[PDB]
Amino acid sequence: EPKVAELKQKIEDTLCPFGFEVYPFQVAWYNELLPPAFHLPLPGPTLAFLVLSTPAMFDRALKPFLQSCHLRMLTDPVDQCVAYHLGRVRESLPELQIEIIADYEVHPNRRPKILAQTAAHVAGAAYYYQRQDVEADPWGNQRISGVCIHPRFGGWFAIRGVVLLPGIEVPDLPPRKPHDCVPTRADRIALLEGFNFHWRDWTYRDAVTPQERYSEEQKAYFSTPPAQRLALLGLAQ
Ligand code: COB
Protein backbone atom coordinates (compact mmCIF):
# COMPACT_ATOMS: atom_id res chain seq x y z
CA GLU A 1 0.00 0.00 0.00
CA PRO A 2 2.68 2.60 0.90
CA LYS A 3 4.47 1.89 -2.40
CA VAL A 4 1.33 2.59 -4.44
CA ALA A 5 0.68 5.73 -2.39
CA GLU A 6 4.14 7.13 -3.24
CA LEU A 7 3.60 6.43 -6.94
CA LYS A 8 0.05 7.68 -6.94
CA GLN A 9 1.24 10.91 -5.31
CA LYS A 10 3.84 11.58 -8.03
CA ILE A 11 1.32 10.84 -10.80
CA GLU A 12 -1.27 13.12 -9.17
CA ASP A 13 1.33 15.89 -8.77
CA THR A 14 1.92 15.59 -12.53
CA LEU A 15 -1.72 15.28 -13.68
CA CYS A 16 -4.22 16.62 -11.09
CA PRO A 17 -3.40 20.31 -11.69
CA PHE A 18 -4.55 19.70 -15.28
CA GLY A 19 -7.96 18.27 -14.46
CA PHE A 20 -7.26 14.52 -14.41
CA GLU A 21 -7.99 12.02 -11.59
CA VAL A 22 -6.04 8.77 -11.08
CA TYR A 23 -7.07 5.41 -9.63
CA PRO A 24 -4.89 2.33 -8.93
CA PHE A 25 -5.80 -1.27 -9.79
CA GLN A 26 -4.12 -4.67 -10.22
CA VAL A 27 -3.87 -5.97 -13.78
CA ALA A 28 -5.47 -9.22 -12.52
CA TRP A 29 -8.78 -7.42 -11.76
CA TYR A 30 -8.96 -6.24 -15.39
CA ASN A 31 -7.82 -9.52 -17.06
CA GLU A 32 -10.21 -11.51 -14.81
CA LEU A 33 -13.33 -10.17 -16.54
CA LEU A 34 -12.09 -10.49 -20.07
CA PRO A 35 -11.58 -13.06 -22.81
CA PRO A 36 -7.96 -14.01 -23.75
CA ALA A 37 -7.76 -11.68 -26.74
CA PHE A 38 -8.02 -8.62 -24.44
CA HIS A 39 -5.64 -9.74 -21.67
CA LEU A 40 -2.66 -7.54 -20.85
CA PRO A 41 0.50 -9.69 -20.88
CA LEU A 42 1.62 -8.89 -17.32
CA PRO A 43 1.54 -10.65 -13.93
CA GLY A 44 -1.83 -10.32 -12.15
CA PRO A 45 -0.44 -8.23 -9.26
CA THR A 46 1.16 -5.64 -11.61
CA LEU A 47 0.28 -2.08 -10.56
CA ALA A 48 -1.74 0.12 -12.95
CA PHE A 49 -3.47 3.48 -12.80
CA LEU A 50 -6.65 4.49 -14.60
CA VAL A 51 -6.59 8.16 -15.65
CA LEU A 52 -9.78 10.08 -16.33
CA SER A 53 -10.52 13.74 -17.18
CA THR A 54 -12.95 15.85 -15.19
CA PRO A 55 -14.80 18.88 -16.61
CA ALA A 56 -11.83 21.01 -15.47
CA MET A 57 -9.46 19.42 -18.03
CA PHE A 58 -10.82 21.53 -20.91
CA ASP A 59 -9.78 24.82 -19.24
CA ARG A 60 -6.69 23.58 -17.37
CA ALA A 61 -5.09 21.36 -20.00
CA LEU A 62 -6.71 21.66 -23.42
CA LYS A 63 -6.94 25.44 -23.75
CA PRO A 64 -3.29 26.01 -22.76
CA PHE A 65 -2.15 23.11 -24.98
CA LEU A 66 -3.78 24.78 -27.97
CA GLN A 67 -1.31 27.67 -27.45
CA SER A 68 1.73 25.38 -27.07
CA CYS A 69 4.56 24.47 -29.43
CA HIS A 70 3.44 20.85 -28.99
CA LEU A 71 0.30 21.33 -31.13
CA ARG A 72 0.39 19.31 -34.39
CA MET A 73 -1.84 18.98 -37.43
CA LEU A 74 -4.22 16.08 -38.22
CA THR A 75 -5.03 14.71 -34.79
CA ASP A 76 -7.77 15.91 -32.41
CA PRO A 77 -6.20 18.38 -30.00
CA VAL A 78 -7.83 16.69 -27.00
CA ASP A 79 -6.05 13.44 -27.89
CA GLN A 80 -2.74 15.34 -28.42
CA CYS A 81 -3.18 17.08 -25.09
CA VAL A 82 -3.85 13.74 -23.38
CA ALA A 83 -0.80 12.06 -25.05
CA TYR A 84 1.32 15.01 -23.96
CA HIS A 85 0.29 14.79 -20.30
CA LEU A 86 0.56 10.97 -20.16
CA GLY A 87 4.06 11.48 -21.58
CA ARG A 88 4.84 13.81 -18.67
CA VAL A 89 4.05 10.92 -16.32
CA ARG A 90 6.92 8.95 -17.90
CA GLU A 91 9.26 11.85 -17.21
CA SER A 92 8.12 12.21 -13.60
CA LEU A 93 9.20 8.63 -12.89
CA PRO A 94 12.44 8.32 -14.82
CA GLU A 95 13.80 5.33 -12.85
CA LEU A 96 10.78 3.09 -13.55
CA GLN A 97 9.52 1.23 -16.59
CA ILE A 98 6.25 2.99 -17.43
CA GLU A 99 3.82 1.91 -20.17
CA ILE A 100 1.04 4.33 -21.19
CA ILE A 101 -2.01 3.53 -23.34
CA ALA A 102 -4.56 6.21 -24.26
CA ASP A 103 -8.28 5.50 -24.74
CA TYR A 104 -8.12 6.33 -28.46
CA GLU A 105 -5.36 3.83 -29.27
CA VAL A 106 -6.22 0.84 -31.52
CA HIS A 107 -4.42 -2.15 -32.96
CA PRO A 108 -4.09 -2.44 -36.76
CA ASN A 109 -7.10 -4.80 -36.66
CA ARG A 110 -9.13 -1.95 -35.14
CA ARG A 111 -9.51 -3.52 -31.68
CA PRO A 112 -8.94 -1.02 -28.84
CA LYS A 113 -5.63 -1.47 -27.03
CA ILE A 114 -7.34 -1.02 -23.65
CA LEU A 115 -10.97 -1.48 -22.64
CA ALA A 116 -11.23 1.88 -20.89
CA GLN A 117 -14.55 1.27 -19.20
CA THR A 118 -13.54 -2.11 -17.77
CA ALA A 119 -10.43 -0.50 -16.30
CA ALA A 120 -12.56 2.36 -14.86
CA HIS A 121 -14.90 -0.12 -13.17
CA VAL A 122 -12.26 -2.32 -11.50
CA ALA A 123 -10.20 0.73 -10.44
CA GLY A 124 -13.32 1.86 -8.57
CA ALA A 125 -13.44 5.07 -10.60
CA ALA A 126 -16.87 4.71 -12.23
CA TYR A 127 -19.37 1.86 -12.41
CA TYR A 128 -19.62 0.43 -15.94
CA TYR A 129 -23.35 -0.02 -16.72
CA GLN A 130 -23.80 -2.71 -19.35
CA ARG A 131 -26.63 -4.50 -21.08
CA GLN A 132 -25.82 -7.46 -18.75
CA ASP A 133 -26.74 -5.26 -15.76
CA VAL A 134 -30.36 -5.18 -16.94
CA GLU A 135 -32.39 -8.39 -16.65
CA ALA A 136 -35.16 -8.99 -19.19
CA ASP A 137 -33.82 -6.12 -21.24
CA PRO A 138 -36.11 -4.69 -23.96
CA TRP A 139 -33.48 -4.46 -26.72
CA GLY A 140 -33.47 -7.48 -29.11
CA ASN A 141 -30.60 -8.47 -31.50
CA GLN A 142 -28.61 -5.24 -31.76
CA ARG A 143 -25.57 -3.67 -30.09
CA ILE A 144 -26.23 -1.94 -26.77
CA SER A 145 -23.00 -0.25 -25.71
CA GLY A 146 -22.31 0.21 -21.98
CA VAL A 147 -21.53 3.49 -20.21
CA CYS A 148 -19.63 4.38 -17.02
CA ILE A 149 -21.09 6.87 -14.56
CA HIS A 150 -18.86 8.78 -12.13
CA PRO A 151 -20.36 9.26 -8.63
CA ARG A 152 -19.41 12.97 -8.65
CA PHE A 153 -19.58 14.02 -12.33
CA GLY A 154 -22.24 11.68 -13.70
CA GLY A 155 -21.25 11.25 -17.37
CA TRP A 156 -19.53 14.65 -17.51
CA PHE A 157 -16.06 13.08 -17.66
CA ALA A 158 -14.02 10.88 -19.97
CA ILE A 159 -11.60 7.98 -19.57
CA ARG A 160 -8.22 9.00 -20.95
CA GLY A 161 -5.80 6.18 -20.43
CA VAL A 162 -4.05 3.60 -18.37
CA VAL A 163 -0.56 3.73 -16.87
CA LEU A 164 1.13 0.32 -16.35
CA LEU A 165 4.20 -0.24 -14.15
CA PRO A 166 5.57 -3.66 -15.16
CA GLY A 167 7.83 -4.95 -12.39
CA ILE A 168 5.92 -3.22 -9.62
CA GLU A 169 3.77 -5.91 -8.00
CA VAL A 170 1.13 -5.07 -5.41
CA PRO A 171 -0.66 -8.36 -4.58
CA ASP A 172 -2.13 -6.79 -1.41
CA LEU A 173 -3.71 -3.70 -3.06
CA PRO A 174 -7.32 -4.03 -1.90
CA PRO A 175 -10.13 -3.77 -4.48
CA ARG A 176 -12.27 -0.65 -4.09
CA LYS A 177 -15.73 -1.28 -5.61
CA PRO A 178 -17.10 1.37 -7.92
CA HIS A 179 -20.15 3.17 -6.55
CA ASP A 180 -23.43 1.72 -7.87
CA CYS A 181 -24.91 5.18 -8.26
CA VAL A 182 -27.56 4.16 -10.82
CA PRO A 183 -28.91 1.17 -8.89
CA THR A 184 -32.45 0.50 -10.24
CA ARG A 185 -33.47 -1.44 -13.35
CA ALA A 186 -35.58 1.38 -14.81
CA ASP A 187 -32.86 3.96 -14.28
CA ARG A 188 -30.29 1.67 -15.96
CA ILE A 189 -32.57 1.15 -18.92
CA ALA A 190 -33.08 4.92 -19.27
CA LEU A 191 -29.30 5.49 -18.98
CA LEU A 192 -28.51 2.95 -21.68
CA GLU A 193 -31.24 4.23 -24.08
CA GLY A 194 -29.92 7.74 -23.60
CA PHE A 195 -26.32 6.75 -24.20
CA ASN A 196 -26.93 4.55 -27.23
CA PHE A 197 -29.68 6.41 -29.03
CA HIS A 198 -29.65 10.06 -27.89
CA TRP A 199 -26.13 10.83 -26.73
CA ARG A 200 -25.85 14.01 -28.81
CA ASP A 201 -28.36 15.65 -26.47
CA TRP A 202 -26.02 15.12 -23.44
CA THR A 203 -28.84 14.04 -21.13
CA TYR A 204 -27.47 10.58 -20.29
CA ARG A 205 -24.67 12.36 -18.43
CA ASP A 206 -27.13 13.62 -15.82
CA ALA A 207 -27.91 10.05 -14.63
CA VAL A 208 -26.70 11.26 -11.28
CA THR A 209 -26.78 14.94 -10.22
CA PRO A 210 -23.38 16.27 -11.30
CA GLN A 211 -21.21 18.33 -8.97
CA GLU A 212 -20.07 20.10 -12.14
CA ARG A 213 -20.91 19.74 -15.87
CA TYR A 214 -18.92 20.68 -18.97
CA SER A 215 -19.32 24.42 -19.68
CA GLU A 216 -21.29 25.44 -22.77
CA GLU A 217 -17.93 26.39 -24.24
CA GLN A 218 -16.70 22.81 -23.74
CA LYS A 219 -20.01 21.41 -25.06
CA ALA A 220 -19.54 23.63 -28.14
CA TYR A 221 -16.06 22.15 -28.62
CA PHE A 222 -17.13 18.53 -28.65
CA SER A 223 -19.23 19.15 -31.82
CA THR A 224 -17.69 16.39 -34.07
CA PRO A 225 -13.97 15.31 -34.35
CA PRO A 226 -13.17 15.55 -38.16
CA ALA A 227 -15.21 18.76 -38.51
CA GLN A 228 -14.61 20.19 -35.07
CA ARG A 229 -11.25 21.88 -35.33
CA LEU A 230 -8.78 20.72 -37.97
CA ALA A 231 -11.42 20.38 -40.65
CA LEU A 232 -12.59 23.42 -38.89
CA LEU A 233 -11.56 26.48 -40.68
CA GLY A 234 -13.95 24.38 -42.85
CA LEU A 235 -16.69 26.92 -42.16
CA ALA A 236 -14.17 29.53 -43.32
CA GLN A 237 -12.95 27.54 -46.41
C1 COB B 1 -16.64 -5.59 -26.95
C2 COB B 1 -16.05 -4.19 -26.49
C3 COB B 1 -15.79 -3.10 -27.61
N1 COB B 1 -15.70 -1.81 -26.89
C4 COB B 1 -14.89 -0.81 -27.56
O1 COB B 1 -14.31 -1.17 -28.58
C5 COB B 1 -14.96 0.68 -27.13
C6 COB B 1 -13.79 1.47 -27.80
C7 COB B 1 -14.01 3.02 -27.71
C8 COB B 1 -12.77 3.55 -28.39
C9 COB B 1 -14.09 3.45 -26.39
C10 COB B 1 -12.69 3.72 -25.55
C11 COB B 1 -11.97 2.43 -25.16
N2 COB B 1 -10.58 2.28 -25.51
O2 COB B 1 -12.51 1.59 -24.46
C12 COB B 1 -15.20 4.60 -26.57
N3 COB B 1 -15.75 4.54 -27.66
CO1 COB B 1 -17.18 5.50 -27.76
C13 COB B 1 -16.00 6.95 -28.58
N4 COB B 1 -17.67 4.75 -29.25
C14 COB B 1 -17.04 3.89 -29.82
C15 COB B 1 -17.80 3.32 -31.10
C16 COB B 1 -18.78 2.14 -30.83
C17 COB B 1 -18.10 0.97 -30.16
C18 COB B 1 -18.48 0.83 -28.69
N5 COB B 1 -18.85 1.92 -27.79
O3 COB B 1 -17.91 -0.09 -28.20
C19 COB B 1 -18.51 4.46 -31.42
C20 COB B 1 -17.82 5.32 -32.48
C21 COB B 1 -19.88 4.13 -31.94
C22 COB B 1 -18.55 5.12 -30.04
C23 COB B 1 -19.48 5.87 -29.73
C24 COB B 1 -19.48 6.52 -28.59
N6 COB B 1 -18.65 6.46 -27.75
C25 COB B 1 -18.80 7.47 -27.00
C26 COB B 1 -18.05 7.80 -25.95
C27 COB B 1 -18.42 8.96 -25.02
C28 COB B 1 -17.23 6.90 -25.46
N7 COB B 1 -16.85 6.03 -26.07
C29 COB B 1 -16.03 5.12 -25.45
C30 COB B 1 -16.69 3.92 -24.86
C31 COB B 1 -15.43 5.96 -24.23
C32 COB B 1 -15.13 5.14 -22.96
C33 COB B 1 -14.24 6.84 -24.59
C34 COB B 1 -13.69 7.82 -23.55
N8 COB B 1 -12.58 8.63 -23.96
O4 COB B 1 -14.14 7.99 -22.42
C35 COB B 1 -16.68 6.86 -24.02
C36 COB B 1 -17.66 6.51 -22.87
C37 COB B 1 -17.33 7.28 -21.58
C38 COB B 1 -18.20 6.77 -20.44
N9 COB B 1 -18.25 5.38 -20.17
O5 COB B 1 -18.91 7.47 -19.71
C39 COB B 1 -19.94 8.35 -27.60
C40 COB B 1 -20.80 9.19 -26.61
C41 COB B 1 -19.48 9.41 -28.59
C42 COB B 1 -18.62 10.45 -27.91
N10 COB B 1 -19.24 11.68 -27.49
O6 COB B 1 -17.40 10.40 -28.03
C43 COB B 1 -20.70 7.35 -28.28
C44 COB B 1 -21.86 6.64 -27.49
C45 COB B 1 -22.66 5.65 -28.34
C46 COB B 1 -22.06 4.26 -28.32
N11 COB B 1 -20.99 3.94 -27.38
O7 COB B 1 -22.57 3.35 -28.95
C47 COB B 1 -15.83 3.46 -29.52
C48 COB B 1 -15.28 2.24 -30.27
C49 COB B 1 -15.35 3.62 -28.32
O8 COB B 1 -16.09 -3.75 -25.06
P1 COB B 1 -17.29 -4.12 -24.12
O9 COB B 1 -17.02 -3.32 -22.86
O10 COB B 1 -18.61 -3.75 -24.73
O11 COB B 1 -17.32 -5.64 -23.72
C50 COB B 1 -16.35 -6.05 -22.80
C51 COB B 1 -16.05 -7.50 -22.94
C52 COB B 1 -15.03 -7.85 -23.99
O12 COB B 1 -15.17 -9.20 -24.27
O13 COB B 1 -15.65 -7.99 -21.68
C53 COB B 1 -15.95 -7.09 -20.68
N12 COB B 1 -16.65 -7.74 -19.60
C54 COB B 1 -17.23 -8.98 -19.66
N13 COB B 1 -17.84 -9.24 -18.50
C55 COB B 1 -17.67 -8.13 -17.62
C56 COB B 1 -16.90 -7.14 -18.34
C57 COB B 1 -16.55 -5.91 -17.75
C58 COB B 1 -16.93 -5.62 -16.42
C59 COB B 1 -16.61 -4.28 -15.80
C60 COB B 1 -17.71 -6.59 -15.72
C61 COB B 1 -18.13 -6.30 -14.28
C62 COB B 1 -18.06 -7.83 -16.30
C63 COB B 1 -16.81 -6.06 -21.37
O14 COB B 1 -18.15 -6.39 -21.25
Image: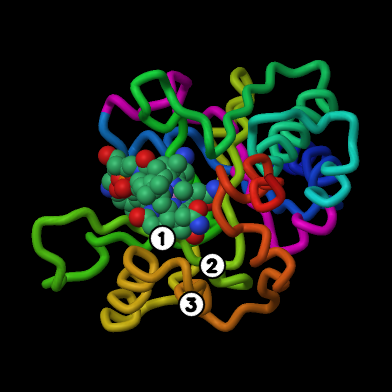
Q: Is residue 56 left or right of residue 23?
A: right
Measured as percent of width and height from the top left, residue 23 is found at 63, 49
Q: Are marks 1 and 3 in contact (CB under 8 Å)?
A: no
Of residues 156 and 219, the one drawn nearer to the viewer in this rendering: 219
Query: Is residue 133 located in the magenta-colored stretch of the structure?
Result: no
Indicate which disc residue 155 carries: 2
Q: CA distance from mark 1 to mark 3?
A: 13 Å
Against 208, residue 43 (above or below) is above
Label 1 or label 3, whichever comes before in sequence order: 1
**Residue found at x 47% / y 22%:** 43
Q: Quadrant of residue 70?
A: top right
Label 2 or label 1, whichever comes before in sequence order: 1
Measured as percent of width and height from the top left, residue 39 is found at 37, 27
Residue numbers of the magenta segment: 36-60
- Disc 2 CB within 8 Å of nearest ligand 1 atom: yes
Q: Is residue 217 left or right of residue 91?
A: left
**Residue found at x 83% / y 38%:** 10
Check disc 3 and report the residue beneath it: 203
